[PDB]
Amino acid sequence: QDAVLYEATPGGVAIITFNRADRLNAWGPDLAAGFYAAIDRAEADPGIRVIVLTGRGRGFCAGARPPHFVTMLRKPVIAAINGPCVGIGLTQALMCDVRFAAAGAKFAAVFARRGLIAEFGISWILPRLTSWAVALDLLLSGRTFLAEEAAQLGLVKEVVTPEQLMPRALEYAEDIARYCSPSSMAVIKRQVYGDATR
Amino acid sequence: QDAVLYEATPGGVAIITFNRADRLNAWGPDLAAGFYAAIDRAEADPGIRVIVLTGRGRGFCAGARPPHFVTMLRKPVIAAINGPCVGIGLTQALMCDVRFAAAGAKFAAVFARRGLIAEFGISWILPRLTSWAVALDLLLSGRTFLAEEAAQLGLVKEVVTPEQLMPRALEYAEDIARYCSPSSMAVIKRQVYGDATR
Amino acid sequence: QDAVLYEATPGGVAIITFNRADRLNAWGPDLAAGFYAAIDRAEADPGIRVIVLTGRGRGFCAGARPPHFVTMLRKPVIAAINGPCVGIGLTQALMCDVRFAAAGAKFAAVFARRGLIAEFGISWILPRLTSWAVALDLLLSGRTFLAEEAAQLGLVKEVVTPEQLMPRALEYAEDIARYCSPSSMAVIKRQVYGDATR
Ligand SMILES: [Cl-]
Ligand SMILES: [Cl-]
Ligand SMILES: [Cl-]
Ligand SMILES: [K+]
Ligand SMILES: [K+]
Ligand SMILES: [K+]
Image 1 (cartoon, rainbow over the protein chains, first blue to last red):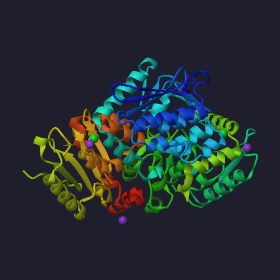
Image 2 (cartoon, each protein chain N blue to C red):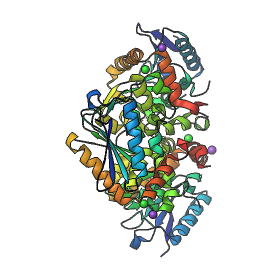
Image 3 (cartoon, each protein chain N blue to C red):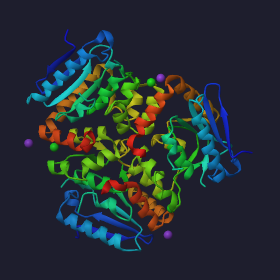
């Protein structure tokens, strides 16, 4: 019944799960507070190496701290996009280090004025991950695109079958946990994002 | 006989047409003045929501205000690239918000020194829409690439058949006109381009 | 027996060849000094228009002046990636203007702390050529990807057969040498990289 579930694997992956499936995990203060507390806990636990972020049920996070605070963590966040990824849900996914998506999962850059203007929000991350052209197209049209188009556009690293989504996100996450030390991951995130988050 | 034609649809799309087909709409002072006046008119008319830009005949704009002034408009410009898009014609296309191209249409980043050095010109927009690598390749080689390669490289949103070019550009344009308010479009353009145009 | 071989074609291409095949051309002070001296020589010779960079044997440069000094040359460098491109070898390839790769050639962004933190190194060039997402994935995973994936990701202009690698890199290089004047190439490199190398 908690808004956000928290689970740690033996391999040192914190699994963070949006748990309001009845509303396709639409953003809200319960979901926010669960998310922050869950992230803080993974971030503070030296036994945790990598974070996996996902939504329970049919949707990832469909509509409704700075927007990009995930980019300033010492630890990587892997989004496993199980279904509808819309509005603030797209913004949060794109703030993550790496994204896997289930085949058929729907994306839409649909926003109210407040999301469009928000500093370090979608109008910041989207063109940085893709380009002005992609960002203009997706924002002005508000159109729906699927996991496969998202991958073509570079919004997603890899599309897998729905059944294989979590095994793959977890495989990859323990893979990087073995390959990089904790201070190497922190260095990488800080080096890649750079001066740009400040 | 006007250098640039102007037409407004019932749906609030201003269609701006380069009308010097005999010279494949090669840039010139007549074409410039028509273009500025036509853009100003669409921009000033509160009945106009979106602008569509195209060339009459076999070519879009093949060879020969700041270069990027289209990026600072309150309203989106959709380029419908019907044929040869070269030199300053490529620069103008790339300054537009969204590009559709006819199958087979030729592109070339061929420039004199003046176009290469021009501030906020092709050496600004090209790598921003693609990358240093793409920009270096296209500029140093001056090579010809077709609509399909342009799409792969992210220079074009979508390739359609020549017959379907204008219907598609207009469909998309009235689509965004319904989806976004005028102040939402203005906000989007300002948020996406950001500090970078100043 | 020289660490780096130097050869000039009639067409004004300087061919620079890493010549420590026994260790897959792994970076080292011999290789560095040969490379700098060879580049300086091409750069100073007004008969030289374009530089081609390659590795003798099975590998390009597999593991181990500022990192990006190639980007500040007046003349283009075309990398012909014949085989394993890893660590500092990936950084050097990516500093080049244009990259061709042999089919099957292995790439890996595998680095010690010193390479990850290095200023204007891989954590600078990689996301600029691709994106934060690609850079985060490749750096945090340290994974191996082949020429074909590298091309999809925009790290490579074109994959050719191993037999056709040098003929193609040289064709392209003499092609650009005919198309651009020397001062036009210098202008292009300076315009594309811009304020960013300073
Ligand atoms: Cl490491
Ligand atoms: Cl809106
Ligand atoms: Cl030229
Ligand atoms: K350590
Ligand atoms: K309004
Ligand atoms: K000259």
